[PDB]
Amino acid sequence: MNIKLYYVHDPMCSWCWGYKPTIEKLKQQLPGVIQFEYVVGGLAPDTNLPMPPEMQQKLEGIWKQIETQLGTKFNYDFWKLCTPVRSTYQSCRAVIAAGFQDSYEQMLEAIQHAYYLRAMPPHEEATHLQLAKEIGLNVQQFKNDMDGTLLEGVFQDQLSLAKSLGVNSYPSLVLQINDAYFPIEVDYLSTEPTLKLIRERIIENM
Amino acid sequence: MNIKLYYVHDPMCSWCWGYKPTIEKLKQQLPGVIQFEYVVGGLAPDTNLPMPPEMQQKLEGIWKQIETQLGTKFNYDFWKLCTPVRSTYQSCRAVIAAGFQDSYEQMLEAIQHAYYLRAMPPHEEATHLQLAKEIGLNVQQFKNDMDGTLLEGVFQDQLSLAKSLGVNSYPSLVLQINDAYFPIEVDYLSTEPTLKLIRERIIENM
Ligand SMILES: [Mg+2]
């Protein structure tokens, strides 16, 4: 029997940044027989149009919700210092490209820190290349990888997979057992109920 | 995947009687893939040696501990009304003979109630016959099965199975997953920690 937990996220998703300490603990605690697979869900298509000011006020107020409920840190200067753009695809391509040099998780964290703490635009090339350097990547290979057809192939496969798993919001977990798929509820604060749900599913399917 | 939970017990073990409501709940709650198997371990070989006063007092003090810790019921008149004998192989034969007529659990409970509640001597043949009659067994067949070499064989095989499973004392639980065996700690007051131990072990071996 073949068992996999998909974690469907976006580097620019606020709740996923709120979820970070728990999903990392979850992945560490998961039994070794379960593969863990990240899937970018692709929160917003490529675009250069600046975010209209109502959408900016909304997203800012969501950061404050997450801070209140989860204790998550945000540098609110992002809304003052940057021109926010509703576009997340480049940041998904950056994490996948970093994954080619075995640094998927290091780049994911670096983009979340950039966006939520460092007041840096997470959709910009300048940010991605500055992060690639900081994280120790071969910057030139990372830049060629971002622009190659191999990466658009991988990226497209993950966007289709997120829709195929039935995911329309982030973060989401889906557990696969052979040919069957089971959504798993996210618990933001604790790993214990999530592991219970996973073990229970596996055992009901034996 | 072949999964089996062995419960190793003796009808005349007083902690097994203290365990009874929890082990019965456990057996009801077990996921359907796990088979439950009773194994008699044979606390003490056949004998007529009278239990002397110091051991009668030690065993009665254990009954009090069990009552204090678990709320278990005892009729202490056993200690005034009977001549106790530490001899349990016959009582193990009796539950196996009742199992030949699909009444293993009914005879096990009738022996516990006879010993702990009815102040009846649990090692005496007259007790076994009386319980066989009270639970509605074919009494003639029960006596033939008790005296036969067939039952002696099944009984010796249980004594060897219990020792093979690593068990010297009761109650004990051992989980078999294919060819691997895992001791599972007993929790006298609830099933939830024990089910979690079982689920964790199964997922850790697949
Ligand atoms: Mg004795």
Image (cartoon, coloured by chain):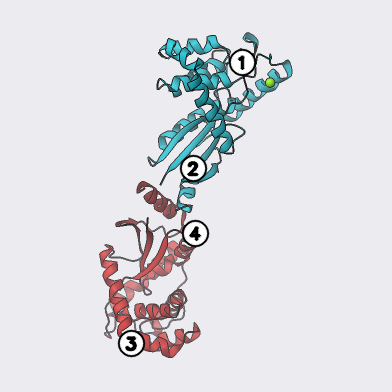
Chain colours: A red, B cyan
Q: Are marks 4 and 3 in contact (CB under 8 Å)?
A: no
Image disc number at residue A29 = 4
Kindly state the secondary structure of the residue where label 3 is placed.
loop
Give the Cα separation between the discs numbered 3 and 1.
Answer: 85 Å
A91 to the left or right of B79: left
For marks 2 and 1 on the same chain, the one whose residue lies earlier in the sequence: 1
Kindly state the secondary structure of the residue where label 4 is placed.
helix
- Image quarter for ligand 1: top right
Image disc number at residue B176 = 2
Give the Cα separation between the discs numbered 2 and 3.
Answer: 54 Å
Q: Image quadrant of residue A155?
A: bottom left
Letter of the chain that mark 4 sits on in the rendering: A
Indicate which label's residue lies in the foreground, 2 or 4: 2
Q: Amino acid at mark 4?
A: Gln
Indicate which label's residue lies in the foreground, 2 or 1: 2
Q: Position of residue B192 (x, y in %)?
A: 48, 41
Camera-side residue of A170 and A34: A34
Image disc number at residue B76 = 1
Q: Are marks 2 and 3 in contact (CB under 8 Å)?
A: no
Q: Are marks 3 and 1 in contact (CB under 8 Å)?
A: no
Residue at the far bottom in the pictured view: A140
> Are marks 4 and 1 in one subunit?
no
